[PDB]
Length: 358
Image (tube, rainbow, N blue to C red; front, top):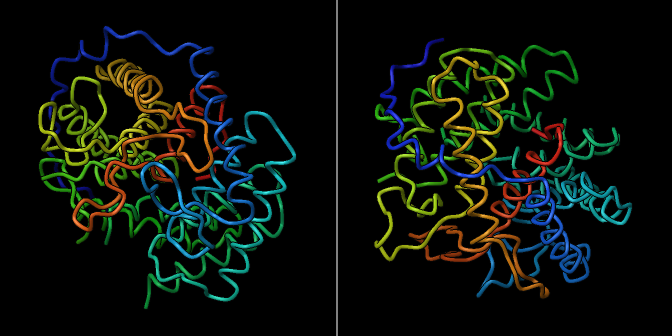
């Protein structure tokens, strides 16, 4: 299958990225340590329960395993575990995994399309880390449910399908791969506009753009279609060209400095992960490769220096100033758990050779 032509905008004023300082080991390390201090605080606060999708006045409420976002909390714990190998983290995160197994076994609150977001950073993550068999079981069950739904289109489905590529690799069953590949091309052609912008379902919502920026290289790993690199370039350049002075996306990329509109830091964290991933594969002769490298550094630096949480009290997020849903008035200028997750994932990506949960 083919990818429709898209307009790849030239990266405007590339020196805005190229003239910046790369992040040092100590800077990233200190950001990770600050994040983990908050996580350890929140461990005692949440116990075996979960943060709400977004904070309220920058304090998460405590909820059970029933939203679309619970996996991102366990994801934070596993990422912390990547850094310090603390058995305490493993023990809590594994209890979450058992809860996720229970959730899929008993079909509890699973009327959410992105089973990938729920099971990948929680269950597939533990499997990646230590081969836990119940984490594997939950993941395969999640994958099977997704397969059933894809026979009985949203941009974040580009991350959703990673669960299918995993199932293909684990079982050898080609059907997982076929559905994954088919859904990729259908999403790419439909949910991405000709100017390389995006909408949610089939102005430019920043997180939707970032889902594409990360979803595409994730899929590229498993498909190796060069037109995916072109599409990544289209979507990424569109994003970078609409970043404000501090390089942190406003919630909608039609807004910039002086708009008075809230930022969405979660979109920027996700884009940093996406660019980091794509750079593993992008040819050295790509004239924009170095610009991308510096871009992701400048974006992540701003998140660390200007947006990361500095108040270490119960319920605080890792990262401030996200937007959950502007139109519903939910989590507007609030921390959110996926933003926390991708922020920490970006830090871990920069710090170590990280084995992807995705």
